[PDB]
Image (cartoon, rainbow, N blue to C red; front, side):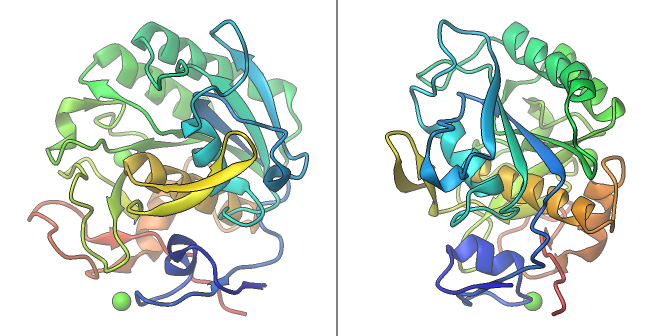
Length: 279
Ligand SMILES: [Ca+2]
Ligand SMILES: [Ca+2]
C-alpha cells in the first residue's frame, strides 16, 4: 500500500533516505494488534480513528482527552491519515490530566492496569503500550515499565525533551523497554531530544502532524511524537509476524536505518526506525 503526500515521519519510516513524501506499507496495517496509549486520553470519536479507538480507563473525573496530547500520539500510532499502523486497535488509558501532567503513582497504576487488562481483550497479533511521558528518575516508575514489558507488552517510551542523557529520566531510563529519541525531517537529532546509552532507537519527532481534540489536526514536536511512531511500527511488524512483544525493540534496532542521523553524541545509537517494506 502507498499513502501519497503523507506526513514526513510516515514517509521517513518507509524510506532509506530523508526527503520522500510517500508512506509505503503492507496493507495488513497492524490489523489484529492492540496499542494502549497511556496519556491524556484519546478522543475516540475523531473520524480519523474509524471506530478503532476506545477509552478503557481513566484516573480522572472524565475519560475525555481535554488536552489533545494523547489524541495526537494515538493518531501517530493508528489514525487513518496520520498513523503508522492504520488498522490497529487503540485503547486509551488516561493517566495524565488535561494540562498534560500526572503523578507517578497514577502513571504506575496505568501501566499495571494495561498488564492486566490485556488479558480481557482480543489482540491476536500482540499488544503494545506507548508512553509519551516521563519526568525525573524514579526506580518505581522504571519497575512499572519493566513489569509491563515482562507481562508480554511491547513497551515504547519517550526519551524525554531535555537535551540531556536519558539515564536521568523515567521511564526512559528503564533498560528493558524501548526508549525512543526524536529526529527531524533533515535527519538531525531533534534539538530537544534526550540521548545516551539507554536509547534504543530514534523516530520522527519534530513537526509531526496528527489528530487533535475537537476533531482537528495539528503539528507538534517532542519525543512524545517519536514514541508512537515506534509503537505503531512494532504493532505493524507484530501483525506481519516478523517479531513479538518481547523482541520487537531489538528487531526494530536490527532493521533500522543506521548512521543516518546528525548530532548524535558518541555512545548514543545512530538508528532510525524503518519498516523495510518491500512491495
Ligand atoms: Ca540512509
Ligand atoms: Ca531498552
